[PDB]
Structure formats: structure tokens, C-alpha cells
Amino acid sequence: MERKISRIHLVSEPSITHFLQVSWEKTLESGFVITLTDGHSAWTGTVSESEISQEADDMAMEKGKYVGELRKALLSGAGPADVYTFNFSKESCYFFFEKNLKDVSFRLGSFNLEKVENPAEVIRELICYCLDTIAENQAKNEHLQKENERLLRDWNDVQGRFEKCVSAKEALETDLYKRFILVLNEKKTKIRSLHNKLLNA
Amino acid sequence: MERKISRIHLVSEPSITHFLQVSWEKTLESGFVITLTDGHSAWTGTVSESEISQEADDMAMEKGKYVGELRKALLSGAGPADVYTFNFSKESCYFFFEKNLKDVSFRLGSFNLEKVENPAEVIRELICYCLDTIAENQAKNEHLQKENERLLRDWNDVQGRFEKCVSAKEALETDLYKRFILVLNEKKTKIRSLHNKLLNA
């Protein structure tokens, strides 16, 4: 059960910002429920899976493409180069969204919404889910920060151990090599002494 | 500028949730603004430093503890062993919160609120602020997730290379000893040949 909420500016009244919520069970392809709120009034509607197919047929485009366009539009997944226009009429109770591009607009979809009995419950539920989401995000952030501290400490310890290994390696190698050049030099001394003096005499 | 939204259950109507937001410039001592809304109408009031100080003096107790209790009550900071009761009267527009304690109630605070002339603006602003909060916290969470994944990968790689470093260190000593022995026997045969030939001659 996934719900998303977004902010949209209606064409009729640019100053105020309406708020649009979509709730779906598992996917938009299976239909969903739409509620539009203004902070003092609200409307609701459904796009049940049965309708979706007929809506796609009317649009005359790929069904997957239509569901993708709806997903990118309603869920504020719009790209920088994509602009969408939503027009809602309360006298006739319609709400249609289109995409504007190259100064020409192509119809995307249209739904009908019936005014709800009491906006208070809708607003209360919206902001309740909001507050719960704040709390959940804060808890997740705290846990992630704790894990981050753990990982940073572990990395620092690993670096220290690796440096210690380097120090041990260098010390051992240099000690052994010096200790052996001593002995080789001693033998070189004796062999030179022999080959020179004992051959001259 | 700091803000905090909380859910409360008024004793006058213990069936619906009312949402109270406290907004204070820097700290609760200077003052704050209380906005209490139930989804249809909102009441806004202000508390300045002078009234908090006067109530603390009337409270017969230190200012710091009074502000601590105020924060614990209004800012949702209540722990397990504490219960608070909020009473709101609309006819007189009078708010006051108390602390229940084994059938003993303390009148912690009594505020006066004035009904706003436009609840839609305030409700929209509240939900807008919360939506911005979620949008900003999601970015932090995803960035922290990315950083933690990167750190885990790097830590795994460094430890894996440390295994090989240590393993090679455990064999360098034999690697050195082999070569040292070999050179020693070679020059030992040299000196032996020299001595044997001279003694024979």
C-alpha cells in the first residue's frame, strides 16, 4: 500500500498551490485512487484497473508508455525538459492533465472527481502520515549514521595495522641485509688477504 | 528559526487529533508562536519572554526547569513516566495544559489564542514545510547510504590486500636466507679452491 503526495499549481489560480495524492496497492497498472485538496476543500476519484485499459485505448498509445507517463507526471518524476499542465474545473468536476512541448500540448489524461463529505479527515490523515514519515526517516538516519561511524573506525584501524605491517617488513629486511653484508665483507677481507699476500709470498 | 509539529488529543473532544506547531526564533526562553489546527479552523497565539518569566515566578520554581517542562510538554519530548492533558475552549478561545499525576493535576500553562481569518493558508504552509522536510531528509539518507556502501567496499578491498601483504611477509625471510646461503657457499668454494691449490703448490 503505497501513497505519494505532490504539490501542483492549477492553471485557474496560479497563486495558491493545490496538493495531489495518489494511493495504489502495488502498481499504477492496477489502478489507484486520487485525492485533490486545497486545505479547505477536497475531491476524490478512482482509476481502477478496468478503466486504465479503456483510457489507454482512447489515448491510442502504448499501454506501458501511458502508465510510464502517468507515473512520471503524477509522482513528481518530471524531468527538467518535460513540463505538464493540470486543469481542474469544479463547476463540472473534471481534472485533466496534458504535456506541453514545443509550444504545442498533447492530451495525456482526464478524470472525474466527486467532492468528499468532510475535508478534515483527509487533511488529518495526510499530515498524520507525513509526521510518521518524518519520524521513520529520522530513525533511519540515526541508524545509518551509527553504521557510518562504525565503518570509519574500522577503516582507520585497518590503515593503522597495514602501516604497522609495512614498518615490520622494512625493519626485518634492512636488519637481515646489514647483518649479512657484515659477514660477506669479513669473508671478502680474508679471501683478498689470502689471494694477495699468500700468492705474493 | 525552529519549528516543531506535534499531535495532541483535546479532552473536550477526545475523538479527533489536533495538531499544534511551536515556532521559536532561537530558543524557547525568548518566546514562541503556537498554531493549533484541527483541519478546518486554526487558532494562533504568541508567547513572549515577559509572560514566560512571569509564569515562572508565579510557578515558584526556577526558569530553567520551567522551560524544560514546557519543552517536554509542547515539543513532544515527553518520556515514559509523564502524562499531559490539554484543554481548549473555543467560545472563549482559551488553551491550557496540565500534568496529571496520580489524580493530582498541575496547571502548567494557560495561553490565549485568536482565531485566524484564513485557515487554508496556514494549513497549506504547514503541509508544505513538512513536505520540504521529507524531501530534504531523503537526500541525506541516500547520500549516507552511498557513502557507507563505498566505505564498505574500500574496507573489504584493503583487508583483502592486507592478507596478501602479510602472507608475503611470512616468506621474505626464507627468500632472503636462500640467496644469502647460496652466495656464501659460492664464495666458500672459491676460498677453498684458493687455499687447496696454494697448499698443494
Image: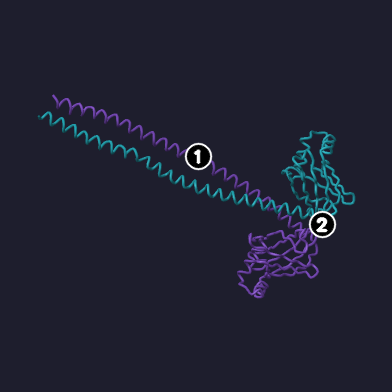
Chain colours: A purple, B cyan
Q: Position of residue B180 (x, y in %)?
A: 28, 36
Residue A109 located left or right of residue A169: right
Disc 1 chain ID: A
Residue B50 located left or right of residue A33: right
Q: Which type of secondary structure does the marked residue at label 1 adopt?
A: helix
Q: Position of residue A4 (x, y in %)?
A: 68, 60
Q: Which mark is residue B40?
A: 2
The residue at 70%/52% (across/down) is B132
Q: Which one is in front, A176 or A97?
A: A97
**Image quadrant assignment for residue B96:** top right
Q: Which type of secondary structure does the marked residue at label 2 adopt?
A: loop
Vertical comparison of B89 with B52: above or below = below
Q: Position of residue B141 (x, y in %)?
A: 62, 50
Q: Which mark is residue A199?
A: none
Q: Position of residue A195 (x, y in %)?
A: 17, 29
* Image quadrant containing the C terminus of chain B: top left
**Image quadrant assignment for residue A169:** top left
Mark 1 closeness class: few <14, some 14–19, many ≥20 residues within 10 Å: few
- Do callouts 1 and 2 point to residues on the same chain? no
Q: Residue furthest left?
A: B201
Residue type, mark 2 in image: His
Q: Which one is in front, B137 or B67?
A: B137
Residue type, mark 1 in image: Asp
**Image quadrant assignment for residue A179:** top left
The residue at 61%/72% (across/down) is A62
Residue B154 located left or right of residue B200: right
Q: Which mark is residue A157?
A: 1
